[PDB]
Image (spheres, coloured by chain):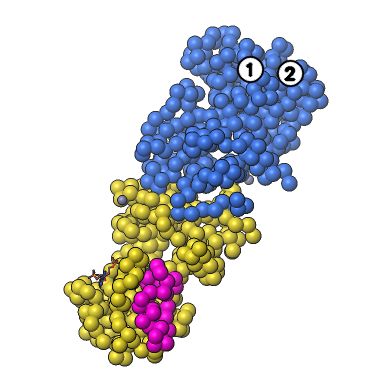
Chain colours: A yellow, B blue
Amino acid sequence: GPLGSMINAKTKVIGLIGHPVEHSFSPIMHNAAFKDKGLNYVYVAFDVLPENLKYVIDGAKALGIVGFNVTIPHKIEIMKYLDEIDKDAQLIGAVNTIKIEDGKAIGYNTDGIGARMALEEEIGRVKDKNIVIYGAGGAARAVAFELAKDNNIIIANRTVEKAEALAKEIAEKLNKKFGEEVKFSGLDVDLDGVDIIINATPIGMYPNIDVEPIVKAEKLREDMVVMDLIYNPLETVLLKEAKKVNAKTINGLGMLIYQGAVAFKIWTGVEPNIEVMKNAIIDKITK
Amino acid sequence: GPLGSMINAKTKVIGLIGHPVEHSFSPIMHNAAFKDKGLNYVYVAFDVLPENLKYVIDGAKALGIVGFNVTIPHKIEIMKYLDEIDKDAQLIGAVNTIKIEDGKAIGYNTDGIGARMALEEEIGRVKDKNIVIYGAGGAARAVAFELAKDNNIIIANRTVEKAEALAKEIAEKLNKKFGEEVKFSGLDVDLDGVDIIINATPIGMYPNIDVEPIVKAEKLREDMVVMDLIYNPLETVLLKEAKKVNAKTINGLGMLIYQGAVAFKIWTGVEPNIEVMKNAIIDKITK
Ligand SMILES: NC(=O)c1ccc[n+](C2O[C@H](COP(=O)([O-])OP(=O)(O)OC[C@H]3O[C@@H](n4cnc5c(N)ncnc54)[C@H](OP(=O)(O)O)[C@@H]3O)[C@@H](O)[C@H]2O)c1
Ligand SMILES: NC(=O)c1ccc[n+]([C@@H]2O[C@H](COP(=O)([O-])OP(=O)(O)OC[C@H]3O[C@@H](n4cnc5c(N)ncnc54)[C@H](OP(=O)(O)O)[C@@H]3O)[C@@H](O)[C@H]2O)c1
Ligand SMILES: [Zn+2]
Ligand SMILES: [Zn+2]
């Protein structure tokens, strides 16, 4: 059909709350998915200052706004304003998706599932495997809490203290063996027997793209899968290093899209077309 | 440009708050005008219950919603949640347009001005004439207050004292003579010598378009002007009753557009294109 949202008096609103948000690809992505499925919703971006976060939930309820996506710096602070919080959300300790229904605002977190789907949808079910997660920030945290449910994960980081702390919280909360199922280490850890490595750090991300990868070619193999959460540029210096060894590369586009796909489902009750989302976003990145 | 609205992460939101709002044509009017001017705004409708009205302004301020239009039944109750209210809306006692600026919510009322422009574009300056206004709601208030500035008016309503109350109030604030310049009566007031009559009541408005007109063609006259504030249908019963006496008829299209046009300017600092607003509405009303 036509390009752009065909708005009328019955159109429902969904928005992204954060500060700043003017560069999010979310609106573009979701509006295309709404059209495709013929749903009468619109996605907009709301720049919310920290002191005003306390007024959004009751405003959304009063207005009839159906839901939100939450990003920096509100995913931790928004939790005290919601009526309920999904377990998967309570575990990670952060909300990035909200649904308002029947006067009840519920928090969710799809960053975890997203990074999983980003993988499975590309290499099938991921259970009982050796997975190394470089980084320990918000991304590595959501990823880890999800892939640790049924996999052996090793959180490697520049500041080990951070790695150790995360591995303990995961083993504890998910009830796993510390030094075995949920390990930690420096960025030096070796990949002998490692099935998949996931880069959850900004190394190689624009504007510092010409820096050396999180791991040289020497430790890379073909029998591996190297996914990079970065998506600017899509093919990082890490994926190059992994291409000179026929490894199955996956760029950040996967997590970004699927993370949204699950939220879409939560708001509309319908599954969105993954290619529409990608084509809308990938077209935004390139000319 | 595109057929629908091309939303991005910078698009600003303007909404209509009221109950109900599903059959409003305002979103149609304004989005059409936004696009024609290349402005990055989207106009949507919010269904707000009277009990939740108190959470909307802080919500709007929090999210960065730049303005609203206010319709039944919040035109008066919203005044207590605003920071400032301009002269007109304060005299009139009702707010139909809001603008959030510098963390400050301001109330305006474009109804009155809208009605005069629509009436004056049709028959030239309206001054020193006898005008009857049927009704006493927010619209009647706006139009009565505005035309009472330089014309003799008579407020006719089913609830007489309610019309008496409004007449006294107008005479009071405009330094007018309660007995002559501003009168009141029931729905059967004699129209001899009356130059213009305006229907500021829902009688005849969709979907109940077969009811009895607020005044029989008996009192109508060929050299009389009959304006109905209803725009859906485009030709109410009152107007086709007026046509059977060759009287000059005017529907509510002009008031709707001119009222919106003034609000448009207020939110954006830009003057919208009238033909665009006008035709966008007609096309959604007719076929
Ligand atoms: N595709 C998607 O769906 C998606 C979703 C979310 C984020 N991303 C992104 O994911 C990546 C990760 O970041 P984040 O925002 O989640 O968290 P974050 O707060 O940026 O996490 C910081 C991480 O970066 C490390 N790090 C930073 N500079 C480093 C360097 N020069 N050398 C070694 N380690 C370094 C930190 O080790 P320390 O703590 O010790 O500094 C830590 O592990 C980013 O590149 C960003 O582009 C993609
Ligand atoms: N075209 C435009 O720019 C524009 C702008 C604003 C409003 N409108 C509209 O203007 C019209 C007026 O209403 P409002 O929203 O301003 O105020 P309101 O709050 O709806 O005021 C109620 C009015 O309706 C009367 N009324 C209702 N049903 C009646 C009936 N069946 N018989 C006799 N009288 C009846 C009341 O007399 P009582 O109080 O005694 O009941 C009173 O005058 C509506 O039809 C609405 O669609 C058009
Ligand atoms: Zn800031
Ligand atoms: Zn309707």
Tell me which residue sits at (40%, 67%) in the image: A232
Q: Is residue A29 above or below residue B214?
A: below
- Chain-order first, disc 2 or disc 1: 1
Residue A274 on image: x %, y %? 52, 70
In the rendered structure, the residue with mark 1 lies on which chain? Answer: B
Tell me which residue sits at (52%, 17%) in the image: B170
Is B190 included in the stretch rendered in magenta?
no
Q: Nearer the viewer, mark 2 or mark 1?
A: 1
Number of marks in picture? 2
Task: Kindly check if marks 2 and 1 are in contact, taking CB atoms under 8 A apart as contact.
Answer: no
Tell me which residue sits at (31%, 91%) in the image: A193
The residue carrying mark 2 is B224
Q: Is residue B169 left or right of residue A84?
A: right
Residue most extreme to the left: A161
Residue B35 on image: x %, y %? 57, 46
Is A252 included in the stretch rendered in magenta?
yes
The residue carrying mark 1 is B126
Q: Residues within 10 Å of mark 1 (few under 14, many from 20)?
A: some
Secondary structure at numbered mark 1: loop
Q: Is residue A141 above or below residue A68?
A: below
In the rendered structure, the residue with mark 2 lies on which chain? Answer: B
Q: Amino acid at mark 1?
A: Val
Mark 1 close to ligand 2, CB under 8 Å: no
Question: Range of the magenta residues?
Answer: A228-255
Q: Looking at this view, is A99 or A262 the one in front?
A: A262
Residue A164 on image: x %, y %? 20, 76
Tell me which residue sits at (45%, 51%) in the image: B10
